[PDB]
Image (cartoon, rainbow, N blue to C red):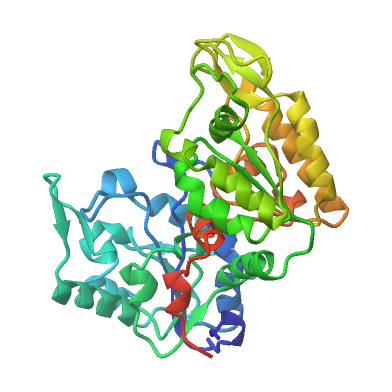
Amino acid sequence: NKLTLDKLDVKGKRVVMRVDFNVPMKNNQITNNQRIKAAVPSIKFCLDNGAKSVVLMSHLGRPDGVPMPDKYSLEPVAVELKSLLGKDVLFLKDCVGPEVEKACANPAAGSVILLENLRFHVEEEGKGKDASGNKVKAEPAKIEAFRASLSKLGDVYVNDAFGTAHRAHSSMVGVNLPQKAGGFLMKKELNYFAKALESPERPFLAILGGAKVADKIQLINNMLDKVNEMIIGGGMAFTFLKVLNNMEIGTSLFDEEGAKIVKDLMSKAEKNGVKITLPVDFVTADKFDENAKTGQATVASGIPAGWMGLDCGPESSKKYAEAVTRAKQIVWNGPVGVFEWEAFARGTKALMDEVVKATSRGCITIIGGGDTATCCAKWNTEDKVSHVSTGGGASLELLEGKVLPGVDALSNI
């Protein structure tokens, strides 16, 4: 088992903390601060408990190992963190090197420091692209030196970067300090998912939605071994329906590879006892546009040639709601329509309504990061579900039954 922050003594200690501050940005400003807010409990605990410093490190975006200060700087995050903490945050223009080590060597007590984007250095990922666009690999001596440098910035290490936990990057697995502790966010996220996977309240419903089938196959198979019911929604559903029901789907997404295995998936579900709920009706569009002409369809009518399905219809929302009603635990990963466009948002919104009502009556409702978490912000329901994950990719890994290097790298207890 793993060391965690609650058991760590930080008094008079410099804490180097990996966080996931890889927040959505637009035009040099933050569009969603949840990832930042999510780390505050760990940071506050360190400060409250006497830490000399807290040195925060993260990536932002995918600069691919070249400094891109004008495009992918973490400077705005520092400003936002200050607002959230109500305490000053010193932003450094790099993450390693002699000046950074000196700045972090013995700061004034209580100092909060945010380093520049780790991914400005190829050593963080271990690979990248040069300024010319060439793929490159980092060199071993250089990668060790990068890790050594980060390790100097603190006396103890905390990893609260749940969002990044799937990445075996230098900041994430390569810090060499005597104590390497999981932070409060890391703990909370893992604990929600482990329980869902291992010991769920039942019935356990998974709601999976998305465009493709092919890239959810490990997810669906693993989940089919854990759940009692599954809703398969969004664009991916058309593959199941074309295969299963001989449905005419028009220009709707169709996954040729996935089509090959739909029956195998259904057969597994039937063997395991899992009830599969697919959509039975749709909102149609003449093209993939917010302002497309719209229509309605059912599995039986088909979708007319040249049209595409972009949301489920009211009959599907009904059927989805029945499954939600039965559930004692829910994991929801994926919207069931093109939620960012009004004409195609009704299915997702209705489903959100149901999940919120479920929570109120004791359902454990866990919302996967990414698009599903985005819907929670959009519709202001972040506090009306049990858990809104900060980590869409990381949580998909957990849902697929895979290990997280970021976790595994922590100190054993």
On the rendered structure, is 76 left or right of 234? left
Decide which of 93, 258 is in the foreground and name it: 258
Number of numbered discs visible in the structure rendering = 0
Decide which of 154, 134 is in the foreground and name it: 134
Q: Residue at 29% of width from left, 66% of height from top? A: 95
Q: Position of residue 306 (x, y in %)?
A: 50, 10
The quadrant where residue 389 appears = bottom right
The quadrant where residue 154 appears = bottom left
Above or below 362: residue 17? below
On the rendered structure, is 339 left or right of 19? right
Q: Position of residue 255 (x, y in %)?
A: 45, 33
Q: Residue at 22% of width from left, 77% of height from top? A: 144
Image quarter (top left, top right, bottom left or bottom right) of the N terminus: bottom right
Above or below 39: residue 312? above
Image quarter (top left, top right, bottom left or bottom right) of the C terminus: bottom right
On the rendered structure, is 25 left or right of 11? left
Above or below 245: residue 390? below
Q: Residue at 66% of width from left, 70% of height from top? A: 198
Residue 82 seen from this side: no
Q: Position of residue 351 (x, y in %)?
A: 73, 37
Decide which of 117, 343 is in the foreground and name it: 343
Q: Position of residue 219 (x, y in %)?
A: 53, 53
On the rendered structure, is 225 left or right of 357? left
Residue 292 seen from this side: yes
Q: Residue at 32% of width from left, 49% of height from top? A: 62
Decide which of 371, 62 is in the foreground and name it: 371
